Amino acid sequence: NTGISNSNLNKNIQSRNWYLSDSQWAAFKDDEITST
Amino acid sequence: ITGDNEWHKLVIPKGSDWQIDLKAEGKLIVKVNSGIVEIFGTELAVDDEYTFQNWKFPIYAVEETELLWKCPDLTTNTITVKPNHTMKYIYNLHFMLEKIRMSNFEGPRVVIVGGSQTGKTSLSRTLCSYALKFNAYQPLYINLDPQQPIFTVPGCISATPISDILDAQLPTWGQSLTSGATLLHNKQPMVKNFGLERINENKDLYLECISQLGQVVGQRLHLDPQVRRSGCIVDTPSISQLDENLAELHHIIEKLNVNIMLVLCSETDPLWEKVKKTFGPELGNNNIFFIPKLDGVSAVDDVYKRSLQRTSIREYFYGSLDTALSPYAIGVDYEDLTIWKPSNVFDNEVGRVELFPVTITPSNLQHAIIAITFAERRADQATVIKSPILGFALITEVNEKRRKLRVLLPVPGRLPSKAMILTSYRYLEQ
Ligand SMILES: Nc1ncnc2c1ncn2[C@@H]1O[C@H](COP(=O)(O)OP(=O)(O)OP(=O)(O)O)[C@@H](O)[C@H]1O
Ligand SMILES: [Mg+2]
Image (tube, rainbow over all chains, first blue to last red; front, side, top):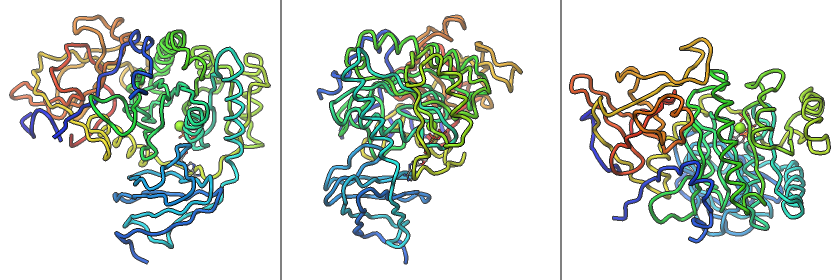
């Protein structure tokens, strides 16, 4: 376990998002991204 | 004569490809001075520096182009520039697909069928790039080849609206949403986890994934006028991987409501008459199109396939060179995990729509990619099989003595208290 450093791995930090559920994804509009 | 760390001029005549095979571990930086060049339909902006690593691809000259390139693993007299005579087929397909988007009630729902390295994924990428290019359509790109990582990791089949330009630098086309500011607008995909290395390992599971993707795809199209008006572009696994009778193609056509078929084969290839005889009564022969061998499409070995699978796993947690992400490492107890494993021909003989429990051991889980469902730890297998995917995690270390695991998450925070699925995919050194 103690092999390397926990927790945030590598100023302005950013991470990958979790995916949306079936309902949320169906109801999603890519214009939410598109602007901007 | 010998690799340099300086810039070199390159004039690509109109209608020619600069064929690149980045065999070595070094980077290639490209800066366009004048003209129009494209990586599978995506135009490279003039004066902007583009960086490429460990992938095979063409830089096509729409117009005579002058560019500068910097790469120490190539010399001026080792460059491969060849004229392309096949783009006409791609444009002609695009403008006919486009005529359907403007005139018909809904956009075309197209399948691309063909053999190993016929140019299926190259055609799909270019059609998506072009769909967006002229009259701004948002087609749904559907990947049904789990070995091919596009917008996600390798265990998946996916549906992704091509809402803005692809990343010309990436073999994965681009990436999913992030928590902050990016140069490009990223994608919002629907991912279904197959998790096994090859389609033949299950099939019933592969077909359930298609059934599940088909359902949500219909729900999105019902609610999204722009995606409904644009169509679908469905990329399938290499034809050899599917049964003789092509029963799996009937399932795909039915589940994804396919109305157009594009066949990538030879003029004397028996595939043409085979497809015409089976899908012609269902789609109508006018709706089945033959695309000859595409120029430049090169063969791909399993070593390059594995190289891409590795790149896409790092890209999931850490991002790309131009977009660095911060994944989160947590220490977890053996007791804090509910992991299931899919049925497969190797372990179970048969390969049924079923999940089996996984016992927490370093032999079972070390360096494994794990799918996180939306289902609660306590949920039964029937609920888990049908549950959507939240994301993926990597199990870096498994300590027997202390009864702990080190898990890498894409999202900083707690370990989601959800049911999980073990994939056949492995990645060493987080
Ligand atoms: N004109 C070209 N010049 C050089 N390389 C090219 C050209 N067109 C395509 N390629 C490369 O050829 C390779 C194989 O093409 P592609 O992935 O589209 O085939 P495929 O039909 O999808 O294969 P598979 O059945 O394995 O999924 C890719 O690495 C791609 O970048
Ligand atoms: Mg492919």
